[PDB]
Length: 384
Image 1 (cartoon, helix red, strand yellow):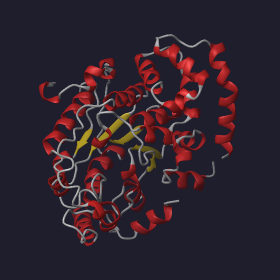
Image 2 (tube, rainbow, N blue to C red):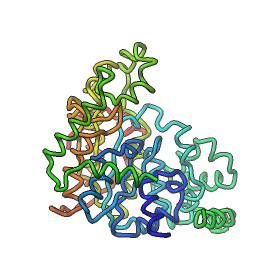
Image 3 (cartoon, rainbow, N blue to C red):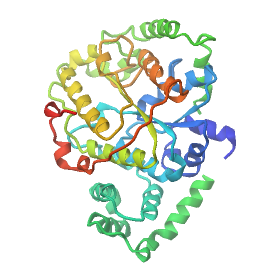
Image 4 (tube, rainbow, N blue to C red):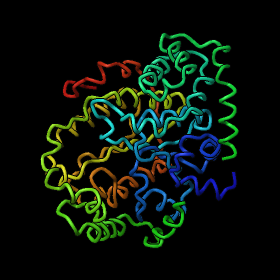
């Protein structure tokens, strides 16, 4: 609970922090820590990363990074729900990755990495009534073998799936294990890189000076391939298979997925907490999609669909960057925001978190977004 430990934790993306309670919930209880949800893009520390800009320009917040490689909506819902009241009324930044929204949803391997018995039990002991969100989550959890290993939990989830509140005597069978997990959590570093990158920035914030610097760094760091990819990413992840990747994504589609309904869990909790949220939708590097055949029209349809889900329920603060696919150096690689992209995000993050302007969101949740109909809905006929 030492302040330097919390600061270190706020940028660690440590799986033990993301699956735990003691550190993240204390930090979220402090006014200064603003949760940034997302996935692996949050580890892209450069001079333009949100934590570097906030530190260099002495802003009144510090991001607490809660995404990590493979964290999608279900895992981040569990983080939010287990924080409970620590999240009430906070501002939130949430990066929506289009790649999460694949036909079969979050890979089992990703779910298993972040599955937290502590946070699952937190939810169960928090429930006072069964809402459609609770029924959906129980239905989802019951499809993962790691959850099924636990017979006591499985029977409780079956009760919730049927719409019934588990009896206290039933939940009490988990209480000993829950308390053990809580004690262990109570008892059991990127700051130097953030500081280093901060020294590369101008003393005074000036967006165009920053843009020029982002273009200079991007150009210097993408010299070994034709696609605008960071050199080490190209060398380690692309080069060995580069011929085979041509046209490999021509039939990929992110418009249909259980992830739309997992994402609805996030929206349910954000609304119940009265969170004000900035959602960010990144593009895919157009030089790369040109090569792989991934359809930009399809990505625009994904964005239309997710924006309908957001806007129809009152989430109207959205930085949609899908149309920045052709902006050099917007992405660091094939999926992760990079120098110009993080700088562009700052143009909406900064006035939100610093309250240059203030708007009030009022939410109207619709449980239809948990349905298979929504998961399979084609975006083109949607109209608000």
